[PDB]
Length: 129
Picture (spheres, rainbow, N blue to C red):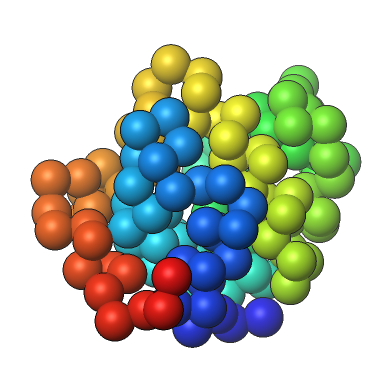
């Protein structure tokens, strides 16, 4: 599923991401835009052989099991394919664990380089939230 901007904002708000660990909704929508272009089916292979999955490009090195990242963990206790669902619940619940891990949303390179320090509430303007 390819979300609309406001559709995703509303879905993330219902799942509790607005102000989660102090990150306003616009931060999360901005990260999803640049990680996956709002496409829940996005996958990308990394140099170390891990793969990023889903709307927030969560990595198999640490967070989910895809059966092909040797010596990786599965800290969200999910198959990585669960992160590709049109239902974003699994991605959101895993993202909550990631952003609580000490480094905040700096865990998302796209957020650091393209959202951090910008007018992120632009990503939710005009939406009926």
